[PDB]
Length: 463
Ligand SMILES: [Zn+2]
Image 1 (spheres, rainbow, N blue to C red):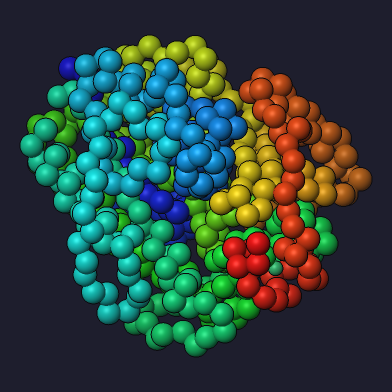
Image 2 (tube, rainbow, N blue to C red; image 1 turned 45 degrees about the vertical axis):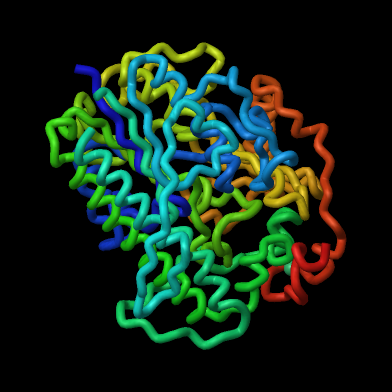
């Protein structure tokens, strides 16, 4: 019998908060239970740390400059994926699967082939944290997926949850200098990489996220207590969505279809979680935002106690071929992803990514400051057109990315070697990166570098 698939994706969800990754306890027990039956990938980099580019890319198995959906802007700034591009939904539908999608779309046409049902917001009251339509829509999504799974073959079902994206609304309610609303639970500690060591040693676009990113403008002058309350809220919205994941899985396993279902849990991108002073996602490529949870379990998938760290994976590219392989569906040769089904099955992985990549372009076209990330087996390299800025982090010895090695002459060979990987990427993927124009108004680079120095309203008000 062909397997069913349930893909659960949570917007902003991070490795740090998912207990299976070993950093934070107590926030994701239902996800951790799935992980404990299957396989989790340590190195799972998304193609862009932003929702619409990530999703347009994910469901088509392509990179953002190829879909040409490079920001969150709507039509005509970004155009829907052409109907001739194969997608996860087209491939599965054409192979006899019922393909259904619940929850957040934000796909710019890459969900073609799925039958989508729009969720309806179901409001509720939270006595300690701000909640908004992000959280209320998730209630509807959960109801929809529960109803579907409680009476389902073969099928592929996506449940696209918003949380912990309600962190964005939290930041708005706590913008600027403020005293935090008291909460009852423990107040988390700041991460080891909270502080930026040296602002002069990071790229211009990253130095001025306070100017270009509304949420960073709002948090720029936050104190340490303020950031700790941010982390608490992030954990709270994570717990909230984890309860919905539990409800969805209970529905799945309530009929005989469940045991024949492969479950995937992932995120479109992560969240700064105060690391590098960052809130949410914008411009930078640090692991908190680019390296997401990527968990599989189900029939034929052999349990692995240890996270898989010997492979570099790219969910944005790899999900489509992995699911097709598990379903016995031929993948178009042009798709650049690499099926992980052999690793999942305990069979020989004959092909793997030598490196993985992420992209930045713009958020809403106020500031266009393209960049690229290359994660090799050990080091992460970043480049930004603006100022020709570069980063180089030793991910083995400096997993917090505190120490930029790009200007250290001891690392000049390593730096060259990673520039060369970017060159290979640009060639093979037909990236127009090197020809792109920076549009970064000097008004958004007009104070001493770094967020504590930020003055004034930021790009969306000034430009
Ligand atoms: Zn600023």
